[PDB]
Length: 37
Image 1 (cartoon, helix red, strand yellow):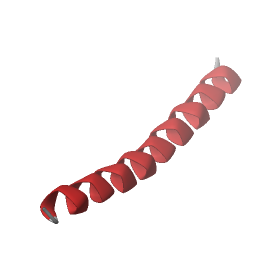
Image 2: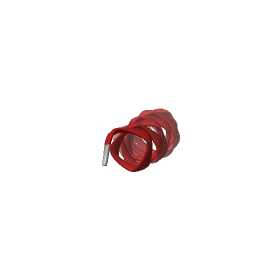
Image 3: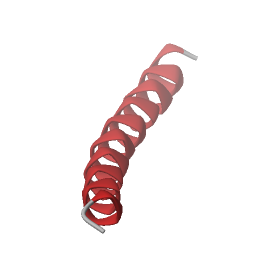
Image 4: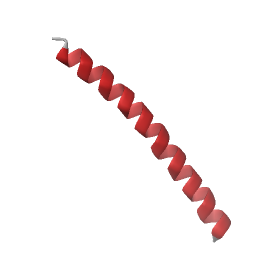
């Protein structure tokens, strides 16, 4: 169904975009911290 699939696509886009920012920031912080030792 078009409206259902457009809503599912919007939720997947939002979830993956948000997760990409969160893991990018967490990974950069953890890697910089580990490297500093």
